[PDB]
Amino acid sequence: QSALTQPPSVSGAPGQRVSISCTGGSSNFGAGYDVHWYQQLPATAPKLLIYGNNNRPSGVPDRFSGSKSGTSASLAITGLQAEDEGDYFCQSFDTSLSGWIFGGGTKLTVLGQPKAAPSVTLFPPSSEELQANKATLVCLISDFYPGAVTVAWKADSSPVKAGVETTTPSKQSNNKYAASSYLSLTPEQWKSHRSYSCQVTHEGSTVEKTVAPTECS
Amino acid sequence: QVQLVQSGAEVRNPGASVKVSCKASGYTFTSYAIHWVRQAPGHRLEWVGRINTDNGNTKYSQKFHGRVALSRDTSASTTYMDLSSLNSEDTAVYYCARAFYYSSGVMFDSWGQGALVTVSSAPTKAPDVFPIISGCRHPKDNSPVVLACLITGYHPTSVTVTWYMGTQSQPQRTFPEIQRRDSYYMTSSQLSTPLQQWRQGEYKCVVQHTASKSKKEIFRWPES
Ligand SMILES: [Cl-]
View 1 (cartoon, each protein chain N blue to C red):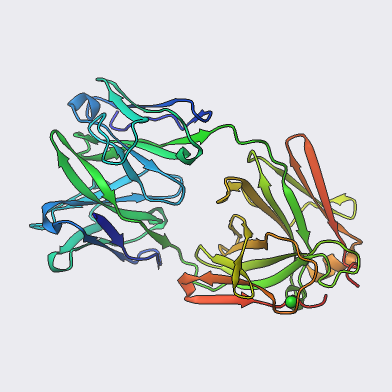
View 2: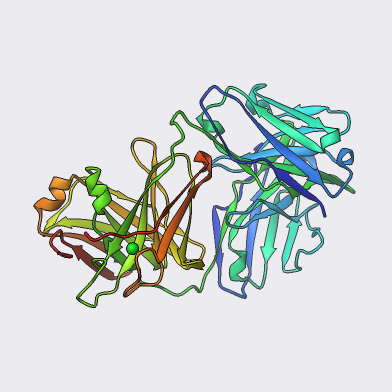
C-alpha cells in the first residue's frame, strides 16, 4: 500500500494509556523512511509530536512516545488527561507516489466524563420574523453527554412530518455536546394550532417543552 | 521564536483561482524549505507541494494536475500558493509548514495557522438576526426568561457571537451551524444565565460575520 493506515479512534480513561498503530507498505515503511506523528487539538493547527520514529521536539512531555518496527509504527500516550482529546496523524514519504503521505488520523477520546442530561429551551417565532412572513420554532439542546440525541416535534398532539431540520450534535468549548432543531412553519400554520412541542430523547430519558401562540398575551 | 502566519479565509467561485500567503519569521528564511498541506472536510491531511526558499525550486503533488503553483518572495520572507481551476473538492483549510532536516530524515516542525478556502457558487451574504425569547419578555408568571438570537441566511461559515450586559461580556451557549437546502446557513446563540427583569437595552447579542465585513447587534426584545 502507498498509504498509511490508522484506527479511526481510540479511547482511554484518565491516567491510563492508549496506543495508536500506523501501518504502511513497501514503498514507504518498506523503503526505510521514518515515521512522524502530529497532534491536532480542536480548532488548532497540527503540531509536531514525534519525529524520526521516537524523538520528541523540545517541550513535548515524556508520556507521548513513539516506536517503529519494519512493518508497524505506534504512538503511545500514558497518563491520559482530558486536554489530550483530539486527532493524531502519522506521516511518512512514499517513493511510488514521490510525495508525503499522512494516515487517516485517529480521534482520541478521554473517558470518564459523566453522563449529563440536556438542558432544553423552546423558542416561539419572533415578531420580527413573523412580520417577514416566516415562522421558525427553535429547540436549543445544550450541556449533554454523550453525543446522541433524538428530536421529535408535535403540532398539538400530532407528530410533525415536515419542516424539521436538526443539527448533528457536536462538542462545544465546554467539552459538552450541543444541538438544535428548527421547525419551519408559515405564520398561518403557527397560529392555526393550539401548541407545538419539541421532544428530546437522551440516555433513557425524554424531556418535552411546549409553546403556544396564545401565551404572552 | 519560529512562527508562520498565513493570510485570511477566502471564498471563490468554481473555476476561479485563489492565492494564500505564508509569512515566516524567527529564523533564516532561505535556510529551510516550506511545504503546503491541505485538509478538506471529511478528508485526511494531503500534501500539496514544496518550494525551496533559496533558489525557488518547486515539487508538486501529481494529484493537482498542474493546477497549483508555489512561489516565494525572499525580501518579504513569504511563500505563496496559487490554486487555479477551483472545484468543490478544493474547499479545505490550507496550511504551510517548515521542513526540518534531522540526522536521517525530514519532518514539518512548525505549521501556519491555516487558511480556509471555500469554493462555492452561492453569493456571500450577511446574516439576518432575530431576538428570540422563552418566557414572554415581561412575565407575570415568575417563569424564568431565556434570551437567544436566531442567526439565518448567511454564507459562508462562520459567524462569531458575543453577549453583553452593558459593557461586560456575558457567558453564552453555542450551537452547531446547519446548512439549509438553499446552501445558506443557520445557527443560534443563547444567553447562558436566565433573567428575571432588565431595562430595555441592557442585554445584547453581537453577531460578527467577517466574510461579509459585517457586524449586527440586537439589543431590544420587544413585546409579543
Ligand atoms: Cl429589551
